[PDB]
Image 1 (spheres, protein in one colour):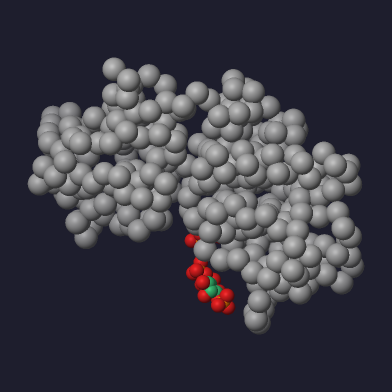
Image 2: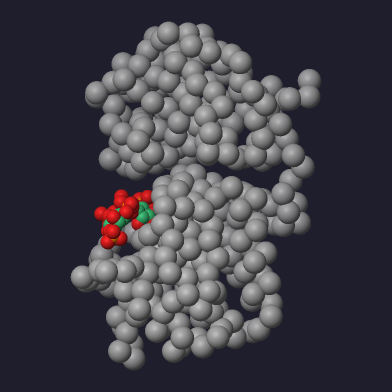
Length: 326
Ligand SMILES: O=P(O)(O)O[C@@H]1[C@H](O)[C@H](O)[C@@H](OP(=O)(O)O)[C@H](OP(=O)(O)O)[C@H]1O
Ligand SMILES: O=P(O)(O)O[C@@H]1[C@H](O)[C@H](O)[C@@H](OP(=O)(O)O)[C@H](OP(=O)(O)O)[C@H]1O
């Protein structure tokens, strides 16, 4: 536990001033005893004391709310699942709400929290810093969040954003602010027609036979493919090229933020986050051309270096699309 804490004026909280007006913190907890969980009573007292009538709180946990009247009802909820991302629609809704609040008084602060004030919190903090003009790139904004939230004098565990889709989504915000005036790009609708996984050896059965793919849109399954069986698909394994190629059938029209989960019947293939071997998010409107290809570092779960004997340096997943217009 080397997150940068606030220990002044009779407070001891897991609370970081990323800037003078932008706070990152963990969940305001109740009935806790206690150590490194912030008691809601103390957090409430902190804001009422140090920023009277000049704070707004952002709760990023889809999983849990709390008594917002402890914060005089100045709480805004962004529903994001642990280890996942907001929809771009929700991210921009958040950005505008923070703008409305921050534009009204130079002394106003925002406090962004989640469960651990790490992944989800960093995603929105880094996006806000881009909006506010402090940084011109997602990489730098993310780097800065990491350096503020991590106290390296306490320990060497990084406390910034690490999961690949969260990094991609801050990247998406950069692209939006640089190319689309801060608003969503033109709607692009797509169908997945193919999936290709390179360096398949050592991953489950190492030939795709154990794998399945679920496409999720707006928190609902919209397609399931089971490879070996030919369930909504046709599998082809190439031993010499160390890759599997699967034709994807019956994919409905996809729009917006799409989560793709890969599941396995292999006991050998460990599960990371999201109760599966690997997954990723993308946005249909930010797809360029007829495909999206993701390297190991860009996929959720293979991003962790402990998996790097399983997912080797050339492990990639490519989705092929047809334009829902041709
Ligand atoms: O009822 P309380 O006192 O709030 O206890 C917490 C509650 O059960 C949460 O659902 C859980 O988080 P998750 O849902 O994310 O597991 C967390 O466990 P954890 O801290 O071990 O995750 C507990 O501390
Ligand atoms: O609530 P947030 O701000 O999203 O923060 C996440 C939360 O603290 C998770 O419990 C943690 O996973 P573990 O507890 O399993 O470490 C995750 O680590 P991650 O960044 O490695 O996903 C954090 O990002």
